[PDB]
Image 1 (cartoon, helix red, strand yellow):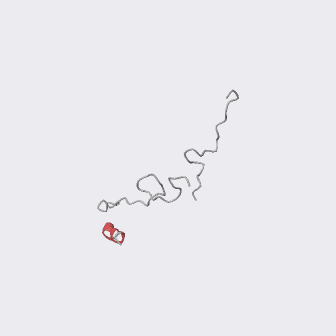
Image 2 (cartoon, rainbow over the protein chains, first blue to last red):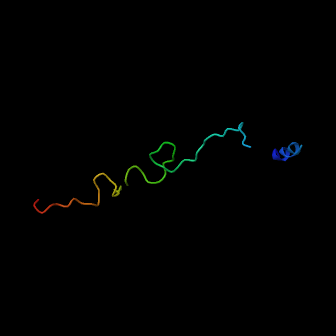
Image 3 (cartoon, rainbow over the protein chains, first blue to last red):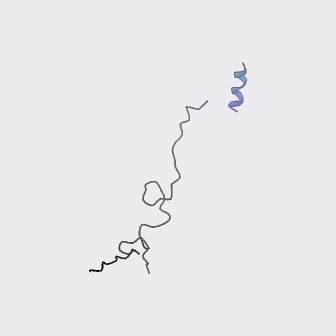
Length: 45
Length: 22
């Protein structure tokens, strides 16, 4: 509905105000910080 | 009862083969 009014006064573009954040779904990785510890273990059992 | 995987420190499957003079 913003674009519904770009055409009316335009008859007569990226939003730089909305700066997104970087949340990331964690990779299933054991060692690396930022990832869940599912899967094969550190000990070999 | 634990069972060690082949990726355990000292539980490899590649056994050390000995030379004939030894």
